[PDB]
Image (cartoon, rainbow, N blue to C red; front, side, top):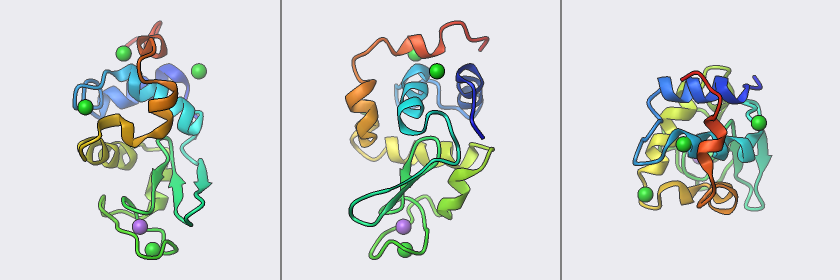
Length: 129
Ligand SMILES: [Cl-]
Ligand SMILES: [Cl-]
Ligand SMILES: [Cl-]
Ligand SMILES: [Cl-]
Ligand code: NA
């Protein structure tokens, strides 16, 4: 599924991401924009052989099982395919664990490079939320 901007903000708010670990909703929308262009089916292979999955491009090295990442962990206890669903619950629940891991949203390199310090509230402006 390719979400609309305000549609994702609304879904993310419902699943409890708004201000989760101090990160306003716009940070999460921005992160998803640049990770996946709001497409739940986004996948991208990493140089190390791991793969990134879903709207927030969660990686198989640590967080999900895809059966093809030697030596990796599955800390969200899910198949990486669950991160591709039109239903964002698995992605949100795993994002919550990742953002709690010590480095906050810096865990998402694109959030740090493209969202961090910017007017992130712009990503939710005009939305009924
Ligand atoms: Cl947009
Ligand atoms: Cl915001
Ligand atoms: Cl594996
Ligand atoms: Cl933080
Ligand atoms: Na894994």
